Image 1: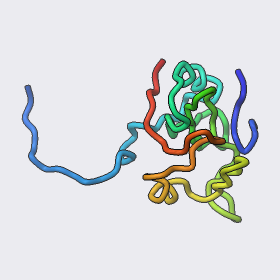
Image 2 (image 1 turned 180 degrees about the horizontal axis):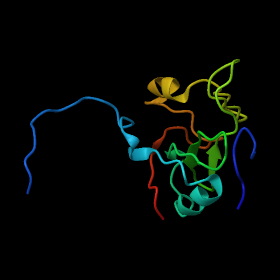
Image 3 (image 1 turned 90 degrees about the vertical axis):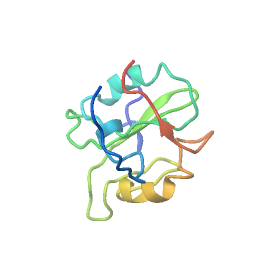
Image 4 (image 1 turned 90 degrees about the horizontal axis):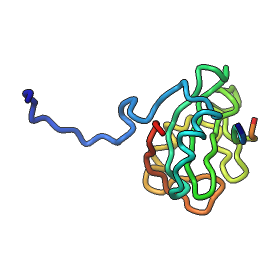
Length: 10
Length: 120
């Protein structure tokens, strides 16, 4: 699945 | 029926593990928290026992759901955070005391937070 994180998605 | 005491307490909502989990990684938690479509702020503070550095703030917004963890505690700050409108790279629990009434939201449409379900 996507998106992963924040600061990005990693 | 069971007995109870009359004692009461004035403490905040985030005073127990009631909104805290650490084995519902970003790919799984977006499947369960993503069937919802509420204001930008329907969040949880969960992580994974899989990403080796995870402490995420996880928002449920009005078009998608996203997670906010990349870096652990540093020496040039505390728990690190860098979102384009949220460079919150210090201990989030100390900032939560200020954010309590008017939070920072997700990359934003609305900004105040509320508490969301862990299950589907």
